Image (tube, rainbow, N blue to C red):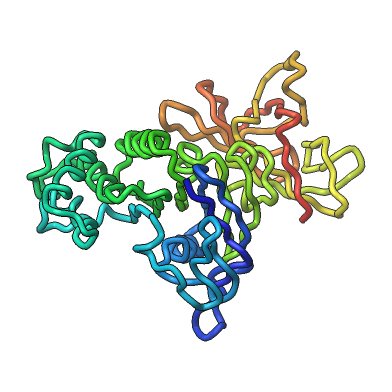
C-alpha cells in the first residue's frame, strides 16, 4: 500500500568516522515483502530506524510514495505521520497495561471517543484471535498470544507499512514457524508493504519475496532468496544465506584443481574460491550413472559426525587438506576412499 524509495542513503556516526550505511539504493514496491539480511553490525537496525523515522539519513533521501519524509540530516515527516506499524526485537508490550490497553494506546490522541476506541481494538483483537484475553496483562499471555497482541497494537491505526526488526529472535525456536506464518497471513490479508530485517536466513526464506544483503553498511546484492542462494555474488553472501563448503584451488586449464579434485569451472585469476553446498555433494564407493551428478574425483573421509538423525561426513581430496562436508543417512567411515560427485550447475566459483 506504500512504495518506499531509498535514495543514496548514508548514515555516519562518531563525527563521520564510522559509516553505518553507505550509499544504499532500493525501491521497495507497494505491497512487497522485502527482507534485509546481514550479520550483526552490518547496519540493519540503523536502516530500519531510518525507514521508521526514528533516525534520518546523514546524506541522501527517503520517500514514501511521492512524499519526501527525510533528507540529508533532516526529519521531514515524523514516525507518527508515516502510517507504519512496528514490531521490534521484543513484543515491547507495556507490562502494566492489559492487552486491551496496549492495543488502545496508539489511539490515545487520534480524536476517537471511548466507544470508537473500544470498537476498533475489539475488531482488531478478533481478527488476530486474542479478543478473549484482552483483560490479561502481558505476563499472563502465552508466547503466541503476546505476538498477536503486539501485532494488533502495530495494526490498530491501519498502517500501509509493517516494519519488523528481528521479530523472531533466538528466543522462540520451536515457535518461530508459527510466528512467521502469522506475519505472512497478516501481510496477505492487508496487502501492506512489509520490511523485515534479520541475521537469520530462515526468517527471510519464510517471509521475503525479495531480499537485500547488507555487509558493513553496503548493499552487496539484491534478489529473490532462491537467487541469492543459488547465485550469490561472493562467498560471504553465499555463506550468509545458507550452509556452504568453501575451498581454495588453482585455476589450471580444465577447471579448478584442488588435490585429486577437479571442478569444471574457471575464473580470470590464478587461484579461485569454490563454493559447493552440502546438499550438492554426494559420496559413493562406485560410479554414479547419472547425468545430474558429476564426478570431480576421488576423496578420503577425514571424520564423521552425527546429528538430527543424520550423518555429517567430512572428506578431503587426495593430497590436499581442503575439506568438504555433506549430509547423509548413510555413514562412511574415516580413512575410506570415495568418489566425490557434485551437481554440475550448482558449483559456485569466485576470484581469490
Closer-to-camera residue (332/182): 182
Residue projecting furthest to the top: 289
Q: Is residue 102 above or below residue 263?
A: below
Closer-to-camera residue (273/334): 273
Residue projecting furthest to the right: 253
Q: Is residue 61 above or below residue 192?
A: below
Residue 49 horizontal side relative to residue 325, left or right: left
Residue 149 horizontal side relative to residue 201, left or right: left
Closer-to-camera residue (174/131): 131
Residue at image location 36% in from the left, 37% down from the top: 186
Residue at image location 56% in from the left, 76% down from the top: 72
Q: Is residue 21 above or below residue 332?
A: below
Expressed as whole percent of the image width and height from the top left, the position of residue 276 reads 67, 38
Residue projecting furthest to the bottom: 15
**Residue 53 lies in quadrant:** bottom left
Residue at image location 78% in from the left, 48% down from the top: 249
Expressed as whole percent of the image width and height from the top left, the position of residue 85 reads 35, 52
Expressed as whole percent of the image width and height from the top left, the position of residue 248 reads 73, 49
Q: Quadrant of the C terminus?
A: bottom right
Residue at image location 50% in from the left, 22% down from the top: 329
Expressed as whole percent of the image width and height from the top left, the position of residue 209 reads 54, 39
Residue 57 horizontal side relative to residue 184, left or right: right
Residue 290 horizontal side relative to residue 265, left or right: left
Closer-to-camera residue (159/280): 159
Amino acid at each position: 500500500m506504500v512504495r518506499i524509495i531509498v535514495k543514496n542513503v548514508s548514515k555516519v556516526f562518531k563525527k563521520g568516522k564510522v559509516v553505518a550505511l553507505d550509499n544504499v539504493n532500493i525501491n521497495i514496491e507497494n505491497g512487497e515483502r522485502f527482507g534485509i539480511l546481514g550479520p550483526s553490525g552490518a547496519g540493519k537496525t540503523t536502516f530500519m530506524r531510518i525507514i521508521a523515522g526514528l533516525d534520518v539519513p546523514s546524506t541522501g533521501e527517503l520517500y514514501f510514495d511521492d512524499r519526501l519524509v527525510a533528507s540529508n540530516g533532516k526529519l521531514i515527516v515524523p514516525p507518527e505521520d508515516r502510517k507504519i506499524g512496528m514490531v521490534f526485537q521484543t513484543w515491547a508490550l507495556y507490562p502494566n497495561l492489559t492487552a486491551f490497553e496496549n492495543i488502545a494506546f496508539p489511539l490515545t490522541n487520534m480524536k476517537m471517543s471511548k466507544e470508537e476506541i473500544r470498537k476498533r481494538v475489539e475488531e482488531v483483537a478478533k481478527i488476530l484471535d486474542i479478543h478473549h484475553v484482552l483483560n490479561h496483562f502481558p505476563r499472563e499471555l502465552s508466547g503466541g498470544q503476546q505476538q498477536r497482541v503486539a501485532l494488533a497494537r502495530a495494526l490498530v491505526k491501519d498502517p500501509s507499512l509493517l516494519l519488523l526488526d528481528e521479530p523472531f529472535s533466538n528466543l522462540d525456536a520451536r515457535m518461530r514457524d508459527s510466528a512467521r506464518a502469522l506475519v505472512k497471513e497478516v501481510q496477505s490479508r492487508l496487502g501492506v508493504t512489509l520490511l523485515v530485517v534479520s541475521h537469520d536466513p530462515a526468517d527471510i526464506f519464510a517471509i521475503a519475496d525479495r531480499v537485500g544483503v547488507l555487509v558493513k553498511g553496503k548493499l552487496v546484492q539484491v534478489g529473490k532468496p532462491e537467487d541469492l542462494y543459488d547465485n550469490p555474488v561472493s562467498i560471504q553472501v553465499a555463506s550468509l544465506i545458507g550452509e556452504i563448503n568453501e575451498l581454495e584451488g588453482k585455476v589450471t586449464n580444465e577447471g579448478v584443481v584442488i588435490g585429486s579434485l577437479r571442478f569444471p569451472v574457471s575464473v580470470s585469476s590464478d587461484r579461485a574460491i569454490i563454493g559447493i553446498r552440502p546438499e550438492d555433494v554426494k559420496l559413493s564407493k562406485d560410479v554414479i550413472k547419472d547425468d545430474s551428478w558429476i564426478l570431480v574425483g576421488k576423496g578420503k573421509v577425514k571424520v564423521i559426525g552425527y546429528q538430527g538423525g543424520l550423518f555429517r561426513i567430512t572428506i578431503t581430496p587426495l593430497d590436499s587438506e581442503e575439506e568438504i562436508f555433506t549430509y547423509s543417512d548413510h555413514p562412511i567411515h574415516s580413512g575410506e576412499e570415495v568418489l566425490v560427485y557434485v551437481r554440475k550447475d550448482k558449483i559456485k566459483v569466485f576470484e581469490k
